Amino acid sequence: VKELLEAGVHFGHERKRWNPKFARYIYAERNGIHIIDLQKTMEELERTFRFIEDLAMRGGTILFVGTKKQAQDIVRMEAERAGMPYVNQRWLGGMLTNFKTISQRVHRLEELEALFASPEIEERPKKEQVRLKHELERLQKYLSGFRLLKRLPDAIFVVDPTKEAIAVREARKLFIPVIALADTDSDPDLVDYIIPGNDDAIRSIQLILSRAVDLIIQARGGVVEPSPSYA
RNA sequence: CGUCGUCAGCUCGUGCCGUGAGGUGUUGGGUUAAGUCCCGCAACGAGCGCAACCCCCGCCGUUAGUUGCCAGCGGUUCGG
Ligand SMILES: [Mg+2]
Ligand SMILES: [Mg+2]
Ligand SMILES: [Mg+2]
Ligand SMILES: [Mg+2]
Ligand SMILES: [Mg+2]
Ligand SMILES: [Mg+2]
Ligand SMILES: [Mg+2]
Ligand SMILES: [Mg+2]
Ligand SMILES: [Mg+2]
Ligand SMILES: [Mg+2]
Ligand SMILES: [Mg+2]
Ligand SMILES: [Mg+2]
Image (cartoon, rainbow, N blue to C red):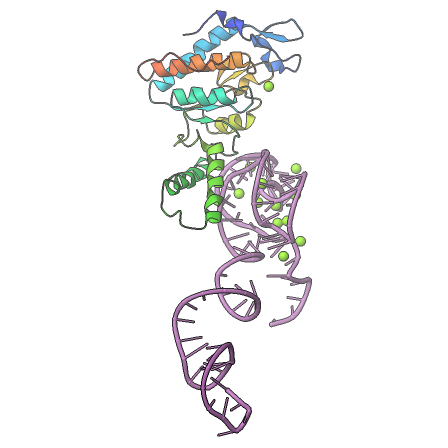
């Protein structure tokens, strides 16, 4: 499922803005840029993909977490492929530790999923009506993938654990496996199942994400091949 | 009942921070008569307030035509 010629997308970056705790996954500092060693990645993917495949094999649920620009749309696709919950735009504080309370915003969502599912009564003030069509969109803008998350997840798969320290901190507090792909600017000790590598190259973000999702399909029966590897 | 003050404010529930008082939310950018609304955000909602629903005034319609009114023909002591 893995590769060895994945070294043709990323092998690391981020020039001397590093976290010293990451040095045990760094091979050399060449063009001003810290270069990640992938023999450290290959062993680690063996751990992570051992965890991911074994997790879906028993009915798990991985909350995929991506927020930044270079990983915005790709995390939407890959989580929808495996039918997995994603958080796309903003990570709402408490989403995990205050789950039974933010989930109270998807019930309001399903409400406007029924209301604007013709008709209940649309014959109630259009102002009072189009008031809601904006509240509808907003809920979809932030709860589009979290809605399928009906219960506190079994693990989370984040794109950037520094950029997403809030989500990590909550999951760590709930004894939730924190699995993540991370480059030279993050804390290995905070990640339960690590994937050392670039998290800014879309050419690399999609790679370790798209063919990680592929592994999730084969663990819940049957395979599919093509996912969006847009150029 | 007066008053501050019809001033835009005062708080709660869960989560987060803090040894603790307490903080966050309610701060920030913009907008409003307004914590009014928008965008942002370790917060997510909620309540009391603000607004609204209520009464008078301003235009039009329906429904009614005496004790009210008189547009147009008839009288008319000349007062519908
Ligand atoms: Mg970064
Ligand atoms: Mg005051
Ligand atoms: Mg509290
Ligand atoms: Mg202090
Ligand atoms: Mg505490
Ligand atoms: Mg408090
Ligand atoms: Mg206050
Ligand atoms: Mg406060
Ligand atoms: Mg205040
Ligand atoms: Mg303050
Ligand atoms: Mg006022
Ligand atoms: Mg706010």
